[PDB]
Image (cartoon, coloured by chain):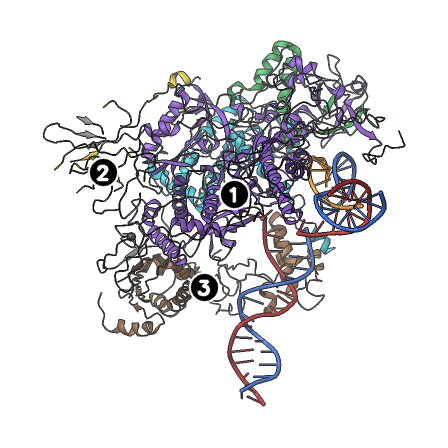
Chain colours: B cyan, C yellow, D brown, F purple, G green, H blue, I red, J orange
Amino acid sequence: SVQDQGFRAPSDTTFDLYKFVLHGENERLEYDSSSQASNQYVVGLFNPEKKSIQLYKSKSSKNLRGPKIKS
Amino acid sequence: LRLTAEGNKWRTDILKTSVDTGREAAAEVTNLDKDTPADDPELLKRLQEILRDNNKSGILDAVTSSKVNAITSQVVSKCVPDGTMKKFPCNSMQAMALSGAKGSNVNVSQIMCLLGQQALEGRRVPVMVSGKTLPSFKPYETDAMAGGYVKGRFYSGIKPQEYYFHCMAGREGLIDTAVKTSRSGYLQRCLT
Amino acid sequence: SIPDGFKKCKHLKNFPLNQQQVWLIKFPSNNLSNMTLLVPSESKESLKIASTASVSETAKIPAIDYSKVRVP
Amino acid sequence: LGIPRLREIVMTASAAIKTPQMTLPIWNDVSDEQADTFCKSISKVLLSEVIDKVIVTETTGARSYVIHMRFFDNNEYSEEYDVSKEELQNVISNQFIHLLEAAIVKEIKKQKRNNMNKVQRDRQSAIISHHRFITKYNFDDESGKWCEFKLELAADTEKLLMVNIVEEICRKSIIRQIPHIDVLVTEGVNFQAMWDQEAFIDVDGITSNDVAAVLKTYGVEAARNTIVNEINNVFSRYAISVSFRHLDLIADMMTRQGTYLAFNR
Amino acid sequence: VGSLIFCLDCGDLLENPNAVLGSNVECSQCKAIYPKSQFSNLKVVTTTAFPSSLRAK
Amino acid sequence: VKDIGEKVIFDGKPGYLGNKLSVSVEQVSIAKPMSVERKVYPSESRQRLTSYRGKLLLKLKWSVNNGEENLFEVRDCGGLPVMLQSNRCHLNKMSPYELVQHKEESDEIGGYFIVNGIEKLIRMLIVQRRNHPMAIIRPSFANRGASYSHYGIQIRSVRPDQTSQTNVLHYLNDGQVTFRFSWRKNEYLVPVVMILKALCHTSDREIFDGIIGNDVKDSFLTDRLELLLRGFKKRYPHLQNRTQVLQYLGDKFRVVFQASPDQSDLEVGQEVLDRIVLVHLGKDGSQDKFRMLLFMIRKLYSLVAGECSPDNPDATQHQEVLLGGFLYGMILKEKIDEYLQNIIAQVRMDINRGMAINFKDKRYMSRVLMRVNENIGSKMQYFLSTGNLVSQSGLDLQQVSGYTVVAEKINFYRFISHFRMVHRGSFFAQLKTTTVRKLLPESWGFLCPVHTPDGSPCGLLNHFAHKCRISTQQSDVSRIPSILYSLGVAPASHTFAAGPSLCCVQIDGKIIGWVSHEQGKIIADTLRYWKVEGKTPGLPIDLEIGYVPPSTRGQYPGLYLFGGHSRMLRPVRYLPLDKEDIVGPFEQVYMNIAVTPQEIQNNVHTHVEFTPTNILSILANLTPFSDFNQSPRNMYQCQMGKQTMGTPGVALCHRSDNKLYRLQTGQTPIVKANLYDDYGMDNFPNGFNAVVAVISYTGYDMDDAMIINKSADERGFGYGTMYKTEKVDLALNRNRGDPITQH
Amino acid sequence: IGDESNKFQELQTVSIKYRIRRTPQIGDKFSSRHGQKGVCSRKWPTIDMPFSETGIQPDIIINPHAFPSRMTIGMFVESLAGKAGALHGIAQDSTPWIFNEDDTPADYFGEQLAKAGYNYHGNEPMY
DNA sequence: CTACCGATAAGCAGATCTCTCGATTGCGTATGAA
DNA sequence: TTCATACGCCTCTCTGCTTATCGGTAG
RNA sequence: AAUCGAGAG
Ligand SMILES: [Zn+2]
C-alpha cells in the first residue's frame, strides 16, 4: 500500500507547495535544488501483526537595518 | 665485469636469504615476536605509529640499514674476487681498482655484486602518508627492497623501483654537492 | 509570501496513526528529521501542517583473471 | 660540525652557547652501578616529565577547577628520575602553583580587555594563603595519584582553555635543575659550581670543553689549548689533520689582546 | 548540551547563567523568555605533551 | 569578461546625484591575419624579426542607467600575440604537406609565441590544488602576530574562469579562529563566525551541529566552539540581524573593494562575500559556502587536536600545474579590468575639472576613448618579452619577474624539452631549504625521476613524464551528484554529521554527502567500475577520484572527486577490465599499482602501468640502457643532450636567428631506443656512430680526455656549423616624421 | 625587411646571416649518450693510430679508467650491441627493463657476435 | 628625601671564486608660440 | 583648444651593539 | 654603464 500526495514548539507552521517545495509561515519564525532521485523519501508505518506495511511520500525581531550609505 | 657460474650461484644463494631481513628488522623494532607474519594487524599498527613519529622512523631505518649492510658485506666478501671469471693480473677493472688508479672496491662491488641499500641522509627512503613507499608496493610493506634495498647490480640492470630509489639517492647527492660547491670562501678571506 | 504561487494541501491526505521508520529509496516503481509533517499534516482535516506527538548499486566487476593478466 | 662550527668558533668568536656537551668516563674507583646515577641526579628534570595526564573539571556550580593531575608509577618514576616524592610535593607547593596561577591571573586580566588528619589541613594553610584561594590536597601513600588543587575564581565562569595553559605551565616548571645544565653523557654548559666533590664517577675528569665557559674563569692562556683542541676535533672527523703548527699560529685570536678576539670587524 | 541547552525556540545561544534572573533574551529577542534555575550547572571534563619517559610500543 | 564587473561612476546632476555609466564588456573576438584583407602565415616576423601578433576585438557597453540607453561599440585594443598551431593561427589544422608548402617545418608544432622574432614561451608553473582545503603547520602563521599558532587551513579556490583566490584560516592560541584573505596587493582579516553568520540566515545551534556532529560528549571541541561563540557575542552585540551583519561588512569594506558611492551596505557586503570567499562555489551557492566552512573549521580543530596529519605543500598530492594559456587569459582579464578602471578614472577627471559631460553622446564617448590607452596587445607583448608580471590583484601568485623563457632551439631535444618543464617558483629558487628539492615518491608517473638540470636550479626544473597529459578542459561534472545520490549516501543538507569519523563526499569543493568509511570505500570502487566500464552518460574517464581511508593520526578522511581544469593525468591499465584508466596524483597515493604484469600479486593490486618506461622523460627514454648506468650519469646525459650540436630543423633557409649550431651530417643510432622512431626523432638526427675503442694507448687521456682519429676528422667526422644573424638598420635614431639623410 | 606600415621610404632595415664552419679542433667537448663527456685531446695521426686484424682504425679513443668511477655499463653494452647491429645489418633496441638477469644483454649480444664470427666479449685483437 | 649606576627586554648596520654569451634600459605631465 | 617638449612621481636568515624598566644604597 | 636570463669551469 503506497500513497502519493533540536527544536519543538506548538503547531504554527503550514504548507504552500508552489510547485514538494514550500516556504511555510508562522507568527514566531519566518521560514533543495539537488538530489534528483534521492528526494524519494517514504514514511514506513508497518503493522507488525503478520506482514502489513504502510507507505507515504526567524523574523519576529529581525528587521533592523542601518543606513544605505555612511558618510 | 662478468662472474663465474659458481660466483653467481653464491650471490643468488646469499641474496635469497635476505627475504626476511626487513620483516625481522620490523619485528625487532616493534618488540613483537621474532616469527611474526608481515600481515599482522598489530604489526601494521606499530608500523603506522613508527611512520607517524620521526624518531621511531629513524630508529627503524637505522636497524634495517644495519641488517641490509651486513647482508651486502657478506655478498661482496663471498663473491669478489673469487667469482670473477677474469682474475686480478688480467682483470683490468679490478686491477685499476686495487692499484687505486681510479674507482674503488665499493664501485667494483656495486658493479659486479650489489648496489646494496640507498641511504637518503640517515634514513632508508621517504614514505607517503599512507605507509606506501611507492605506488608499486603494499602499504606498510616489510620488504627491504621496498625500503630502498637494491638487490640488483649495474651489470645485469635494475628493476624500475630500484631505478627510482637510485635516482632519489643520486639527486640527494647532487643537491648536497651543489650546495657545498661554494659553501664558504669568506672564512678564508677573513683569515688571510 | 508567495514565491510563485500557493497550491496548498487543501486536498488533505489522511494517514492515521495511534514502529515507524523512514525507508528512503532512489527510484523504484513502488534528530535531523524536519520533514516529519508529510504523514501528520493536520489530523483535523484543515489546511495546515502540525507537528506530531542496499540502496547503493553494487554492480561488481570482481575476480580479476590472474591466470589471464599475469603472463610470465 | 664542519664549516658551521668552524665559522662559529673562529669567524665571530661566538661566546654564545651553541652546543657544549658534558662528558665523563669512569674513574676506575667506582663501579658502573653508581655510574649514570650522578648524571641523572645532575640532569635537568622538569615537572612535565613526570606528568601522565591532566584532568580539568570546570564546574559552573561561584566556579570550580578540579585539576586532578596524574603522574607515573611512584617507584617507576623514582627509579627513572632520582626525584623524591617529597621533593616533588615541595616544588609543586612552592613554585608551580604560585608562578603559574599568577600567569593564569595575567591571562584572566588580559581576557577582560579521601580523609585527612589535620596534617593535610596544615599543608593547605599556605596553599590557601596563595593568591587564587585554591583548595589543594595531595598524596598520602607515597604514590602520585592525587595532586588536586581546586581553583575557584568567581561567578564570572569565563570560558578558558585551562589545559592549553597548563601544558605550557608544566613545560615551564623545573623540578631540580642547576643553572646551565640540561659515555654516560649528559648535556649542559657550566663551569662555576660544576666543581662538585669529585667522588661519584670520574668527577675529577669531566669536561664539556668549549670556549663558552672555559676562558671566563677556568684559565686564560687555556685558550691556546681549548681553541686548538676544538678546531682539531673538527678536522678529526674526516681526518684531514692539518698540522698543529697552524692551529697554534692561530693565536691572534687570544694572545694579540686580552681574551678571545675574533677574525671580523 | 555542550555548554548550554539552547533555547528551544530559536537556534541561538543564551547568555551565561550568571545574570539577574532568567536571561533568555538576546537571540532576536527569542520571542520568548522561559525562566532559569532549570539547569544545575555546567561541567566540561577535559584531559591533556610529556614525551620524556613515555615508553610504549 | 562577463564576470569582470560593473564599474560605475555617477554624473554630477543636481538623494539623487546624476546618471550612471555601467560600463561593461560583452565579447572578445579573434583576428589572425593582417592586411584589401590578406592572410599572414608564420615565418613572417621571423624573417622580418618582429612579432607575430593577431588583433583583439573588444565590445563594451555604455548603459547610462538600468536598461535605458545602451551604446554598444566595437573597440578593438591593439594586437594580441597569438600562439602557433593554436586556434588563432593560420596553421591550425594543416596537412604536413601544406606546412611544407607554407615555408614551415615538415612537422612543426609549438606553443611558443613569436615576439620580435624571438619565439618565447610561457613556462609552466605548479601551485596548490583548486578546491581542496589543506592543513599547514608553517611557523610563518604563528609569526604573523601575537597568539597566532602554526596551524591553519588553506584553500586556493578558483572561479569558473580559473581565477585564483586564497582563503586562509589562521588559528589563534586564545581560542578564536580568524578568517584571512587578500584583496588588491594587501591583506584584510576578519573573524570566522562573522562570515559564517553573514553567509546565510542561520543560527548558532545549527553552527554547533555543523562543527560537531554527534560528538557532543567531546570536551575539547565543545569548549573551543563555545569560546568562539561567546567571543563573537561579546565582541559584536549589536550585529544580530543577518542584514545588519551584511551592512557591517559593507561599511567595513567600502574603499577596500572600490565600491561605488551609490551602493547599499547590504549590497556591498553581499558582493564581497560573493566575490572574495569560496569563489569556486560561485554565486547563489552561499548555502554551500556556509556548508564548506563548517567542514573547513572541523578539520582545523582536528589539526589542533592532532587527529589529522598535516599535508605537505610541496608534495605532488596537493600540487597542481597551471598552463601557459590559463595565465595568458588571467592576465588578459586583469588588463581589461584595468582598462575599464582607466576609462572610469578619465571620466572622473573630466567630472572633476572638465565639467563638459553628457553620458549619452557618441561624440562624448569618442572623446573619452580617444584619451585612454588601447595598447592591450602591446602590453601583452611586453609581458611576453620581459616576463615582468604587473597587476593589482597579483593573481594569488608568488613570483613577480620571470614567466617567459627564450625557448631556444639549440637542439631539437632542448626545443621539445622546453614544452615539458614545470617550474616550482623563483621564490623557492631563492630559498635555501633542501627538503623542497627532494624527489618525493608521490611524483611517480608524473615528473621524470631523471630529467633535472644539475647545478643551481637542480631539484626545481622538473619535467613531466612522457605520456602524461594535462586536462585543459572542465569535464561534464553536472550529473555526477545525481548518480552519486543513487548509491547509498545522505544529502549534505538533510542531515548534519561532521568530523573525520564520517567519510565526507565532495565534488570539486561542493560538500554533497556524508557516509561511513566502509561505504565510502565501496562507493569509490563502484565509481571506478563505472568510470572505466564506460556506458554511462556522466563520469568522464579522466575523473580524478580519491578516497582517503580512515587513518590513525593520518590524513583527513573523506571521499573526493575532481572534475578539474588543469590537474595532472596518467594512463594506466585497470586489472578488473584490462582497459585504459586515467589516474591523478592525489588519486595515486592510495592505489596499488604494479610496475609490471609479472609482479601483480593477489588482492594487492588493481592497476599495472603498461610499458614501465612511461614513467620517464622523453629525453630520458632516449638514453640507451638507462638501467645499467649511474643516476648522476643519467642526469648528466639528460643535461648534455640539450647542449648538443643539434639539428635545429630543415627550414633553416629562412629562420633568421642569433645562433643555430647546425650539424652537417648525422645518423640514426644503431642501438636506438624504442620510441626513438615513435616520436619522430629520426627527422632530427644528431650525433654519429663512431667505432670506439676502450683502450689506454696514447696516454693523452686519463681523466676525461679523448682522442679523435686525424684522418677520420679529415673525412669530415663531425662538421657542425654556426648560423648567426644580426639586424642592421639606420632608423634606430630616426623618429616618425624625420626621414634620415643617410641610406 | 620592409616596414609593417606603408613606410615605403628607402628600406633602411636589413638582416643578414653569417655562416661559421666549426671543424672539431682539440678541446672541443664530445660525449656519448651516458654522460661520458670529454674533450678532444689530440688529432692522433691515422698511421700512429692502432689498428685491428680487419684493418679498421678506430676514430674515437676513450680511456678505460673512466668507467670504474663513472660506472656506466651502458657505454659497454652500447658498444657491444652497436658492433652486433653494424655487422648483422639489423637495428638494436635499447629500452630499459627489457633484459632480466636471466636474459643478460651481454649474453644476448655475445650470441649475435659469435654467430657473426667475432669475439664473444667484443675483445678484438689489435696491433 | 634622593643621585647615581648596575641588575633587568629590544633598534641599527652589517654580512655572507673566475669566465663566456644573450637580452633589456620604469612610468608620468606642464608651458607657450601659433 | 591644441601642439611641442622640458619636466616629473609610487613573499621563508642571523649577529653584535642603539637603546629599554627598575630598584637599591649610602649620602 | 648598469639590471635580468642562459650558462661553463
Ligand atoms: Zn531564542
**Crowd around label 2: few <14 · some 14–19 · many ≥20 (10 Å):** some
Q: Which mark is residue D218?
A: none
Q: Under tag 2, what secondary structure?
A: loop
> Label 3, label 1: how many angstroms apart (C-alpha)?
31 Å
Comparing labels 3 and 2, the label whose residue is closer to the camera = 2
Disc 1: CA contacts within 10 A as few (<14), some (14-19) or many (>=20): few
Say if disc 3 is inside 8 Å of ligand 1.
no
Q: Name the chain letter of the residue that bears numbered label 1.
A: B
Q: Nearer the viewer, residue B159 or F462?
A: F462
Say which amino acid is labelled 3.
Ile
Q: Chain of mark 2?
A: C
Identify residue type, mark 2.
Answer: Thr
Q: Nearer the viewer, mark 3 or mark 1?
A: 1
Give how far across and how far down residue F465 sits, in percent. 55, 27
Q: Are marks 1 and 2 on the same chain?
A: no
Q: Residue furthest right?
A: F741
Residue B97: image location, x then y, percent = 64, 32
What residue does disc 3 label? Answer: D42
